Amino acid sequence: AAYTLPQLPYAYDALEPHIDARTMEIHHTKHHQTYVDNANKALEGTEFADLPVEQLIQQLDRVPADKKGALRNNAGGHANHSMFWQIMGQNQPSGELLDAINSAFGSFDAFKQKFEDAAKTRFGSGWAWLVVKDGKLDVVSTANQDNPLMGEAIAGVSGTPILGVDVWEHAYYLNYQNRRPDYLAAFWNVVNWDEVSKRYAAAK
Amino acid sequence: AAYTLPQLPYAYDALEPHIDARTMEIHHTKHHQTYVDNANKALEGTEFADLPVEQLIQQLDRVPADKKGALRNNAGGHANHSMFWQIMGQGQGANQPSGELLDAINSAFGSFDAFKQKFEDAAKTRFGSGWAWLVVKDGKLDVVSTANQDNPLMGEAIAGVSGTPILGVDVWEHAYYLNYQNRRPDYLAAFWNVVNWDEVSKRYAAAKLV
Ligand SMILES: [Fe+3]
Ligand SMILES: [Fe+3]
Image (cartoon, rainbow over the protein chains, first blue to last red):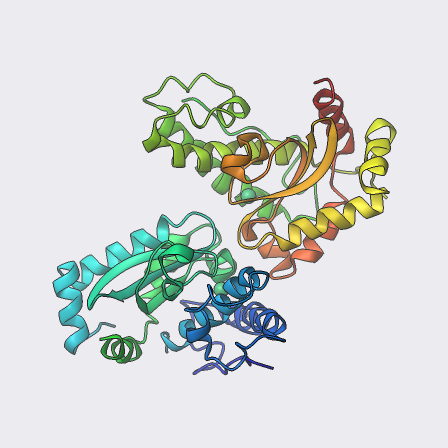
């Protein structure tokens, strides 16, 4: 009962042809639903069912030892997907965020290449992230459903994500099959930079 | 180059309807090919180019530290898929083993049906990308799983498990997504129809010879 599946900000076909509608529906109603269901099961009987998911995943070292794995995977899955839907919409940043991107990466085009590289070289399942770390932007990747908010010890990297892309094969296989780089190029067309900017201002 | 893409023992549509022809083709000519190509790149400037792949993956500590990850992933990828193609077949068998292998399964797991349950459970609980395996470990059968392209031959320190694999199923989403989408359990149930138990039994007999 802790978490519910969030509604999408747009119809399943709103991100076409960049992301197919069938993928959106399955990704949402099956994959994301499963993380919600399994996180809920894991949270029953604990003192952690009342925390927002993004706070729970920052407290994985405090949960019961036998629940840590399940919560890392499933609360991570829920946090990651919840953000993912919101940072897309039906294309460049501006204002303070663009300035930060320019400073950290040289240019928006250079940032894109770095972000794409991190996504491409992530072997197996996982995510690539733009994070705010000590007030500065960086590009990182994580395995499976790990999130940089989980911290160094668990996720391998840290910082507050403001943008992420799902590079699990489920995110792209129906439309792109093996062609992850084509998926990643097409992703830039659906990023909601207004939402990413809101998250940057917040993280700063 | 050190490695080449092996030919399949059957046509791309030979495992229909259990595994779709399109998947077989892409899995073979794109995914497996990429593992071959990238392994070949990492081996180009080394003394490891002449080893059979199954020996190379057993020697990953020996390799230069800067090549270790690349070889783990890509040599592992090549070893895994090379075995995968050989342990499936068309018009097999319900499909099940017999003889010494079946006796060993009954001994280790209680029955073939119990083994299937245990193997499906290991494959289902492998979170993210990886493989489930039937291994011979100290002369006895066990069911284990690995992450990504890790293989039990790599040893416990690298792969988290050990033993000689005699059967494995690919549970990377690319192995099943076109035909089954999220339904990994449906894929796993169909997989039993294409296992070549004659080949698995050959590998068992060899593994038990010490
Ligand atoms: Fe996903
Ligand atoms: Fe594969």
